[PDB]
RNA sequence: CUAUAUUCUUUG
């Protein structure tokens, strides 16, 4: 981890003042909204598609 | 009278949107009303149709590889489709060059290909062209196909990868598709791989032409016409924009008078100059009207006769042209009855400024012969779409076309060049919505000066008269 | 079943083999077999697929390239860039006119009417639906002077034709003239009148 | 010619050639003005399926069933708007189309063209005028029940 | 010399604007993996998409590695999160492939023979298989230029 | 500063004699002056009336006098 | 004042003398055999453009007082 | 090297052409994508990216009141109830077109009004705040140690006259976190910039001053 | 590359669609494929490029 | 070695070019000419070899007047 | 073909809780039809259509207001990009709008989209983020 | 009074920004010694206004 | 730095 700017991004200094510019708590993919279809034609079955997995889990 | 400047009444409206805009509007207003009739192609089109297959053809060109920057070269002979192509190229922003077909060799074709460097070439297999037998003009059928194979011999050599090779002729590497326009009367269409898809929805989510039309601007040039008498050695084809065309047609349409679905004709072979290419069909579009084509051609006596016989059936309230072809009508007009022409009321001739001065007693001959209420004469250089000033048969005074400034200045300034003394030879400069400062050349798209006062150089020398009158001249050579 | 070469051998080669080195027999080749595509194996239709399939030149950060190809080459580059900037801006203004117009259901007009933009700036929920104006309200005239007609008042001088409400001035100037400066040239650039000129006192 | 071939599907029920659009390969494209009145609907399939009895043992019905389901997934009807589709009955909803490109009128009057005779039986002329999975029909011919 | 090192914590989200690794020209130490690009001259690895960077080691020789970037971050996050939460409840298995200690064993129990499938030299005839396969359409690809297994 | 090249032998922002550098006058300020009652809407407003009513101090006045900007004023 | 007085040249002058306050000689043709020879050479120097009757200097000051606008809205 | 491929042909909306034949002996855009000799094109180079447009700035010459800042004031346990937000804004445009409007309440584009008076009678505000000679509200934003050009700022509230401490004690509820001092002439609020000046001016306008 | 915020800006770049970039074996002896033979094929020179690069094809 | 490739169409535009050792060799007395993108024309043009330091628009860059077959 | 009928027809879901705007009788009828139906359809087939003039005349004949499809966002962002001066995107300050100091050694930071405001953002910790909203609904960068 | 603002800076830099943050910006010289045979990218890394290093800016 | 390069590109 040696080097000057590596020291500058730990103590977060002038260029790096807000470090990692990509952190957890951003996802470029789902934009933090829940993908589900509540748009079911009949309002009866509204939750019919639920827990359709997003990945292997 | 005193100083050389001329101005039209500025009270008439100007149309500044794209062409596609007015096509859509006119489509929504009069959908079923007629737009253009052509008997010999069996073409009867409403505004519905002009819109529908304009943008349909546009998508066709998109799928044939055309993109907003590039150019299209068109050798077509007085068809419906050269105009449809104008609208199509307008929609995708491609410059459409229309070149005169009457004298065409492999040589000047290769010249055009070197100049415009077009992506598409719209040509025929067989094209009809005038030529002289025993001192008499007759139609010949030229094989243009042969010509294309002369210019590009490499299409004759076929190895079975070659449809997909990246560059089809190492000579012209920009040439991609050649669209052949010819009527084949067999009921079965062509197979889907020699044909472009012109119909139905082209997408799912949004029609991409209207995404694209946001990036297009009314002054983006789309057209190029050959100038028979080039102002300089340099200016070869003069170039028009959306604004130029639409406003030319609207000014003509307004200045005459035109009412919805009144019938209004055009003499052929004018689609290469701003009569059939610009003024006529955009007049018919801007004011609800119905354009009518007579017989496909002019030069031979037989289809002059055929022409008149057609024009009396089609009920034309008035028609357009140039003197040269009105001679042909004049010859064979005597052979018919005085009352066959009773629907014809007015007629119009457009005049290049290098003609000079169509004689008025000739107009008198026209009106007395066809039982014409009135003859209108329009005049101007080619960058004006042949309209700067205009006169009637009853009014010999030359009035300026509305929104046009013509001034003749000295040589020592650009914006601030001073007006001259009204008889003096000097530099002619025009200002108006349908005037164009663009021109096309071996180099590319070029422009000459458009200054801070708003005028634009034509690089032409001119003389103004005391009464409203312009006379063009070549560069002064002392 | 299987073959030693894994595909049926075409009769030409066979007959050419068992009559040694001679093919006079079948020289007319049958066309290759077809590969069918499953149209429902294809992925669902996407919007971005529709945006970018055309591959327009406007998504470049270098500048507006579609603008450069639609523009005269005559113009010296440094003055040409800010020309292309002017048309690309005018296209923006027009765009926003179409947007605010469709927003208020008004038939389009451009420079823009004021009341439209200012009173549509007054609603956060008005971005949901847009309506077309009736086919009657539709006209060819997109300039206000031709649309709103005459109103009672004026300010600028009566004598000047350049000030007339309906007067038409070209939207942008075009000069063939070259630019006077570039960073790689040493003495290049414009000088104050009483500054020493270039190569002065040689 | 495996790498160069024009796309050919075995079922155009989605009318894919209208949406997925490949450039005509040929250097010379033939385009008239006469074809603007031509209507481009996909070539008639073999084994017209609208007549298939939906027996649970039949091969063609099974294969058409699963086709339709895959289409219904690709246009995002099935999991989304209609989470459970039990496909039993073979449904054909047809419209009385003339294959008319745009909306027309009468020459003798200027009236709207009179409502067409309601279709009695299904024909080959009637095929693309029905509702298959995802296909396209001109608005002009959807104008009546 | 200069020291050439990671400009991001490995196993951490990263934006396309940052250099991932700077290598030094000796085949490089780190080769571009999924969603990563490498400068032809500088051999400096940049990220294409915005995602979570991880180091994959070649099964064959552990001293040759790939940098990978996982496009969606939240997957990796709630995965590692649940994993840790379980680690502390003793409810997690150590038999997963994330564990450096066990990866060899894991590759061995899945595909036991992968050594000899690597050592295998195809003769010229099955490297170069006769073109008419590709022409008649029995096979849809002709690729003589991969004789080598990178795994 | 010797690692940095010269640009434009005058210099980047450079004054020369007869460069037009206007001191900005925000329409906001002017309108505010009118509604507050410094100035007459009735009488044609010159630079003189602006100076007398004190809406601009002397230190702001220099040749050429002033530019009229619209800042945050939509009508 | 521009649109009325300034933009019009002197009623006497032709193309070449247009910019002068009053025409400096009678005839508009180049006056001296030297001036004429110069003009001929100028017209064949530039290829033959319309305005070339009037001599323009080959060199420029590059001074900010004589410069006009490069491009922009009109 | 024979240069060819099916990539020369346009394909719209999905590519159904065989994928082995796209580029033949020509570098794909995927090959130049992985091989680029520059690195990391800047975040400003994303053109499609949807950028924010600032609202109209609150200046000393232009009072543009934002309903939500005012909502930031209304959530607070202040005493001395505030006029509702509608009243701090001048009369409308098409309402003020003709001559039928009064002189004091005239329409202003800038937006300007003479003080409204207290939002409630039967109550006495402990302090009184004087407007400027131009009618500007009191707080000025300075910089502590400007010779260094230090980004750290404070707010000096001067024309306050009355019991200044009650003023301070409402000022406590507006800026709970910041540091506050009183002096006979003026009140200091530290670590508060132009934002703070905007709140303050909203509170004073809405207070009837 | 010059973005739009630089001091200078160039014209439109060459359209990708024409005059393509051939994929050519690296001429550098270190970067050249081992088995690559120096291309001696004794051949009557064919001048036009069209037929010339059909030579590099096996389509039969 | 360093030479200049100046557009055969005279835009005055040139590009620095370092001759390969074959062209560094005097084995041929011909000027190298190469197709390039010309920025000024936005087109593909032919470029010729020329000495680097010298005016790139000479009086000698003038082409003789050519009458074009097109039009009247 | 009535008005109220159209309003109900456009918002239709299959089994509704309540239904309004329609006359009572029709509501009762619909309630019956829905009670008889299962949530699950036994055949599904679907077609696609594109706009034409007959649409217009459907809204105009009945005196309704024909809906319009909204212009595209990405085109708006593209135009707004190419519109702005080249100096809009240059570096205008010591500090990125985030508050980080940008030293000039690094080319990623040589351009700046949003103007940096050094006197704004001090109040955000005491306020709701609703305050951060721009004119177009996008949060503007504040110094923190 | 102005003794210390000397023009060697005023030829080189230009100072830019909102009060309390002001960069001084200059172009980079790699330029007029060797342009040729390098690469286009690093060649036009020249043409951007960049801020100078903060030490130098404080110094001036 | 001074000269030679004067359209986007170029020397010592």
Image (cartoon, coloured by chain):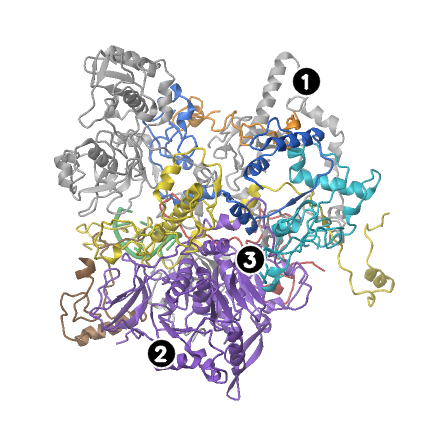
Chain colours: A orange, B purple, C yellow, D cyan, G brown, I red, K blue, M green
Q: Are marks 3 and 1 in contact (CB under 8 Å)?
A: no
Chain letter of the residue carrying label 2: B
Farthest residue to the bottom: give it.
B134
Mark yes or no: residue C88 visible.
yes
Rendering quarter of residue C117: top left
Crowding at dot 2, Cα within 10 Å, few <14 / some 14-19 / many 20+, comes out as some
Chain letter of the residue carrying label 3: B
Q: Nearer the viewer, mark 2 or mark 1?
A: 2
Which mark identifies residue E93?
Answer: 1
Q: CA distance from mark 3 to mark 1?
A: 61 Å
Rendering quarter of residue K122: top left
> In terms of depth relative to the viewer, which is nearer, K11 or G13?
K11
Which mark identifies residue B61?
Answer: 3
Q: CA distance from mark 2 to mark 1?
A: 100 Å
- What is the x, y in percent for residue C73? 39, 58
Side (left or right) of B332 relative to B235:
right
Side (left or right) of H17 relative to C194:
right
Q: CA distance from mark 3 to mark 2?
A: 42 Å
- What is the x, y in percent for residue H114? 23, 26
Q: Which residue is mark 2?
A: B358
> In terms of depth relative to the viewer, which is nearer, H174 or C144?
C144
Q: Which residue shows up at 21% across the image and 64% down it?
A: B418
């Amino acid at each position: 981890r040696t080097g000057v700017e590596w020291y500058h991004r730990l103590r977060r200094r002038g260029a790096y003042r807000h470090w990692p510019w990509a952190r957890w708590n951003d996802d470029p993919v789902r934009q933090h909204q829940e993908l589900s279809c509540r748009r079911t034609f009949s309002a009866a079955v509204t939750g019919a598609n639920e827990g359709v997995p997003l990945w292997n889990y | 009278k005193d100083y050389s400047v001329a101005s039209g009444s500025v009270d008439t409206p100007v149309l500044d949107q794209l062409v596609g805009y007015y096509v859509n509007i006119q489509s929504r207003k009069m959908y079923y009303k007629d737009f253009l009739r052509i008997e010999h192609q069996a073409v009867r089109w409403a505004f519905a149709d002009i819109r529908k297959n304009s943008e349909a053809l546009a998508h066709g060109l998109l799928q044939t590889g055309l993109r907003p920057g590039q150019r299209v070269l068109a050798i077509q002979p007085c068809n419906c489709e050269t105009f449809v192509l104008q609208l199509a190229c307008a929609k995708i922003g491609a410059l459409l060059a229309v070149v005169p077909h009457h004298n065409i060799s492999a040589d000047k074709l290769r010249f055009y290909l070197n100049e415009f460097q077009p992506h598409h070439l719209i040509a025929r297999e067989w094209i009809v062209v005038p030529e002289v037998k025993q001192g008499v003009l007759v139609e010949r059928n030229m094989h243009f196909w042969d010509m294309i194979y002369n210019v590009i011999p490499e299409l004759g050599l076929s190895y079975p990868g070659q449809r997909f090779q990246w560059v089809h002729s190492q000579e012209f590497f920009f040439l991609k598709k050649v669209v052949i326009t010819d009527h084949n009367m067999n009921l079965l269409g062509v197979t889907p791989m020699r044909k472009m898809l012109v119909w139905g929805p082209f997408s799912y989510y949004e029609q991409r032409l209207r995404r694209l039309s946001a990036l297009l601007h009314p002054d983006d040039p789309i057209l190029a016409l050959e100038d028979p008498h080039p102002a300089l050695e340099d200016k070869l084809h003069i170039t028009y924009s959306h604004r130029n065309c639409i406003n030319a047609g609207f000014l003509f349409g307004n200045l005459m008078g035109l009412k919805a679905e009144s019938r209004f004709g055009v003499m052929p072979n004018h689609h290469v100059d701003p009569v059939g290419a610009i003024v006529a069909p955009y007049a018919a579009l801007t004011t609800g009207a119905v354009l009518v084509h007579i017989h496909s051609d002019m030069f031979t006596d037989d289809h002059a006769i055929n022409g008149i016989e057609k024009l009396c059936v089609e009920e034309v309230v008035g028609m357009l042209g140039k003197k040269s072809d009105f001679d042909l009508l004049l010859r064979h007009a005597g052979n018919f009855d005085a009352d066959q022409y009773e629907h014809l009321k007015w007629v119009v001739l457009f005049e290049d400024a290098s003609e000079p001065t169509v004689g008025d007693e000739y107009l008198q001959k026209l009106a007395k012969e066809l039982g014409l209420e009135d003859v209108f004469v329009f005049r101007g250089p080619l960058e004006s779409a042949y309209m700067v000033m205009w006169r009637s048969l009853k009014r010999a005074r030359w009035e300026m076309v509305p929104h046009v400034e013509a001034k003749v200045v000295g040589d020592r300034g650009t914006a601030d060049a001073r007006i001259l003394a009204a008889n003096t030879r000097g530099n002619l400069k025009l200002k108006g919505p349908h005037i164009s400062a663009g021109y096309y050349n071996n180099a590319g798209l070029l422009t000459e000066l458009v200054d801070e006062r708003g005028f634009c150089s034509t690089s032409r020398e001119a003389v103004m008269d005391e009464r409203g009158q312009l006379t063009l001249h070549g560069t002064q050579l002392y | 079943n299987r073959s030693l070469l894994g595909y049926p051998l075409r009769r030409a080669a066979a007959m050419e083999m068992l009559y040694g080195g001679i093919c006079i027999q079948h020289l007319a080749q049958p066309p290759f077999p077809l590969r069918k595509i499953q149209s429902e194996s294809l992925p669902p239709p996407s919007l971005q697929g529709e945006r970018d399939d055309l591959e327009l030149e406007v998504k470049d950060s270098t500048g507006n390239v579609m603008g450069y190809r639609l523009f005269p080459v005559n113009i010296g580059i440094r003055a040409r860039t800010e020309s292309v900037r002017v048309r690309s801006e005018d296209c923006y203004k027009r765009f926003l006119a179409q947007k605010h117009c469709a927003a208020a259901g008004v038939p389009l007009q451009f420079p823009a009417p004021s009341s439209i933009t200012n009173s549509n700036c007054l609603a956060t929920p008005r971005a949901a639906s847009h309506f077309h104006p009736p086919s009657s309200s539709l006209s060819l005239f997109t300039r206000p002077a031709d649309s709103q007609g005459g109103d009672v008042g004026r300010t600028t001088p009566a004598d000047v034709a350049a000030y007339h409400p309906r007067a038409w001035r070209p939207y942008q100037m075009l000069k063939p003239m070259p630019h006077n400066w570039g960073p790689a040239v040493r003495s290049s650039g414009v000088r104050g009148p009483h500054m020493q000129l270039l190569q002065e006192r040689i | 010619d495996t790498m160069f071939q024009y796309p050919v599907y075995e079922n155009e029920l989605d009318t894919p050639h209208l949406f997925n659009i490949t450039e005509p390969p040929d250097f010379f494209v033939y385009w008239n003005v006469s074809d603007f009145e031509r209507t481009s609907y996909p070539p008639l399939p073999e084994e017209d399926h609208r007549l298939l009895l939906p027996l649970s043992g039949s091969a063609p019905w099974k294969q058409h069933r699963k086709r339709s389901l895959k289409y219904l997934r690709k246009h995002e009807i099935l999991p989304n708007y209609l989470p459970h589709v039990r496909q039993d009955v073979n449904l054909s909803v047809v419209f009385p189309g003339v294959y008319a490109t745009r909306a027309r009128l009468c020459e003798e009057t200027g009236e709207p063209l009179p409502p067409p005779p309601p279709v009695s039986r299904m024909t080959h002329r009637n095929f693309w005028m029905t509702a298959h999975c995802g296909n396209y029909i001109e608005l002009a011919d959807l104008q009546h029940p | 010399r200069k020291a050439k090192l990671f400009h991001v914590v490995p196993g951490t989200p990263v934006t396309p604007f940052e250099k991932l690794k700077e290598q030094r020209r000796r085949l490089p130490e780190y080769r571009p993996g999924n969603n990563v690009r490498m400068d032809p001259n500088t051999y400096t690895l940049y990220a294409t998409k915005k995602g979570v960077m991880t180091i994959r080691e070649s099964r064959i020789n552990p001293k040759y590695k790939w940098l990978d970037v996982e496009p969606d971050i939240q997957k990796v996050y709630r995965s590692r999160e649940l994993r840790r939460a379980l680690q502390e409840r003793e409810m997690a298995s150590m038999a997963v492939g994330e564990n450096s200690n066990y990866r060899v064993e894991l590759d061995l129990l899945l595909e036991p023979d992968w050594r000899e499938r690597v050592m295998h030299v195809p003769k010229a005839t099955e490297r170069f298989k006769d073109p008419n396969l590709f022409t008649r359409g029995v096979v849809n690809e002709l690729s003589p230029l991969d004789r080598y297994s990178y795994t | 500063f010797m690692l940095a090249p010269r640009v434009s032998a005058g210099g980047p922002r450079n004054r020369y004699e007869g460069k037009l550098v206007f001191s900005p006058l925000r329409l906001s300020k002017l309108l505010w002056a009118i509604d507050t009652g410094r100035i007459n809407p009735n009488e044609v407003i010159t630079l003189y009336h602006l100076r007398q009513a004190n809406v601009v101090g002397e230190r702001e006045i220099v040749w050429p006098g002033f530019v009229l900007i619209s800042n945050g004023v939509r009508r | 004042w521009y649109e009325d007085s300034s933009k019009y040249a002197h009623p006497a002058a032709g193309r070449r003398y247009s910019h002068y306050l009053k025409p400096p000689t009678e005839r508009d043709f180049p006056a001296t055999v030297e001036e004429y020879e110069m003009v001929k050479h100028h017209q064949k120097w530039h290829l033959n453009q319309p305005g070339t009757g009037t001599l323009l200097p080959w060199h420029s000051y590059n001074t900010a007082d004589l410069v006009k606008r490069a491009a922009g809205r009109l | 090297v024979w240069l060819g491929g099916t990539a020369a042909n346009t394909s719209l909306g999905r590519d159904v052409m065989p994928s082995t034949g796209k580029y033949i002996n020509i570098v794909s855009p995927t090959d130049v994508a992985a091989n680029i000799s520059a690195g990391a094109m800047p975040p400003e180079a994303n053109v499609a990216a949807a950028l924010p447009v600032p609202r109209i700035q609150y200046s000393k010459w232009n009072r543009a009141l934002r309903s939500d800042v005012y909502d930031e004031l209304l959530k607070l346990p202040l005493r001395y109830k505030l006029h509702d937000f509608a009243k701090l804004c001048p009369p409308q445009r098409c309402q003020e077109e003709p001559e039928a409007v009064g002189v004091v309440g005239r329409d202003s584009a800038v937006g300007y009004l003479p003080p409204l008076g207290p939002a409630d009678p039967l109550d006495t505000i402990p302090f009184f705040v004087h407007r400027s000679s131009n009618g500007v509200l009191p707080g000025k934003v300075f910089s502590m140690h400007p010779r260094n050009l230090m980004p750290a700022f404070y707010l000096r509230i001067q024309q306050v006259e009355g019991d200044m401490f009650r003023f301070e004690e409402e000022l406590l509820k507006i800026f709970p976190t910041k540091k506050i001092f009183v002096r006979s002439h003026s009140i200091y609020v530290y670590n508060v910039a132009l934002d703070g000046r905007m709140v303050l001016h909203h509170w004073l306008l809405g207070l009837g001053f | 590359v010059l973005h739009k915020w630089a001091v200078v800006s160039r014209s439109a770049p060459p359209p990708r669609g024409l005059r393509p970039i051939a994929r050519t074996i690296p001429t550098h002896p270190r970067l050249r494929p081992v088995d690559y033979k120096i291309p001696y094929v004794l051949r009557t020179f064919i001048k036009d490029r069209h037929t010339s690069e059909v030579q590099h094809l096996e389509n039969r | 070695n360093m030479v200049a490739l100046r557009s055969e169409a005279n835009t005055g535009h040139m590009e620095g070019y370092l001759k390969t050792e074959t062209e560094r060799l005097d084995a041929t007395g011909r000027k190298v000419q190469k197709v390039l993108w010309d920025p000024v024309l936005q087109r593909h043009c032919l470029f010729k070899e020329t000495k680097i330091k010298g005016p790139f628009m000479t009086k000698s860059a003038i082409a003789k007047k050519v009458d074009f077959p097109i039009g009247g | 073909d009535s008005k109220a009928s159209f309003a109900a027809r456009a918002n239709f879901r299959l089994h509704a809780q309540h239904r309004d705007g329609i006359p009572s009788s029709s509501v009762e009828m619909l309630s019956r039809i829905e009670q008889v139906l299962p949530p699950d359809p036994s055949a599904v087939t679907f077609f696609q259509t594109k706009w034409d003039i007959q649409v217009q005349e459907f809204y105009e004949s009945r005196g309704m207001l024909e809906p319009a499809a909204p212009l595209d966002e990405e085109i708006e962002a593209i135009l707004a990009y190419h519109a702005r001066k080249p100096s809009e995107l240059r570096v205008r300050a010591r500090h990125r709008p985030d508050g980080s100091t940008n030293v000039g050694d690094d080319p990623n930071f040589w351009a700046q989209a949003e103007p940096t405001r050094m006197m704004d953002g001090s109040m955000l910790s005491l306020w709701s983020r609703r305050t951060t909203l721009g004119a177009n609904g996008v949060p503007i960068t504040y110094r923190r | 009074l102005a003794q210390h603002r000397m023009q060697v800076w005023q030829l080189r830099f230009k100072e830019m920004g909102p009060p309390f943050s002001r960069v001084w910006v200059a172009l980079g010289g790699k330029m007029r010694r060797r342009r040729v045979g390098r690469q286009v990218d690093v060649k036009d890394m020249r043409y951007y206004w960049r801020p100078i290093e903060p030490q130098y800016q404080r110094l001036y």
